Image (cartoon, rainbow over all chains, first blue to last red; front, side):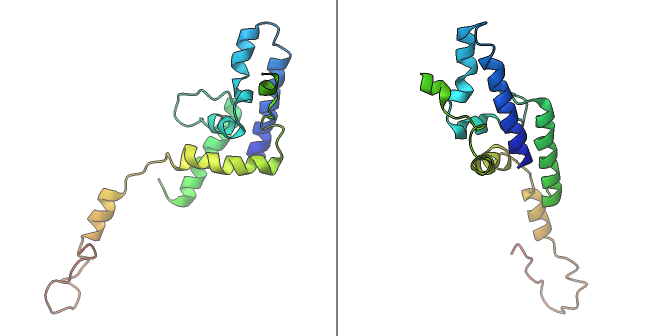
Length: 81
Length: 67
């Protein structure tokens, strides 16, 4: 609940930062709006690329260090360590 | 393409409708892509006769759990 709420707020903030900055470059805006043009399942599949270090997800690092901390506790609970 | 820009992102979907997508995306992204190597230890522990000769069997070698 908290993770999606923080991610949903960030996805609206990162949409506003493009919708009030689209007149700098139309072509760059057309490339930054592919996230919002993509289907909702694909959006959350690409926003969940915190793992490894390819790091194509535009999610902030402070939200990144929340799932990355929950996932360690989940494996501590599961005994995988 | 105006509609293409305006399909509702996840920030417009209801909270539960996005939690239900997170539950199924997190799986494939992290849980399904998580690797841990226990095969060489499980088989090593399953082929060990655990104190069987000390155990009062007074008979032939009992088959190990792997057997």
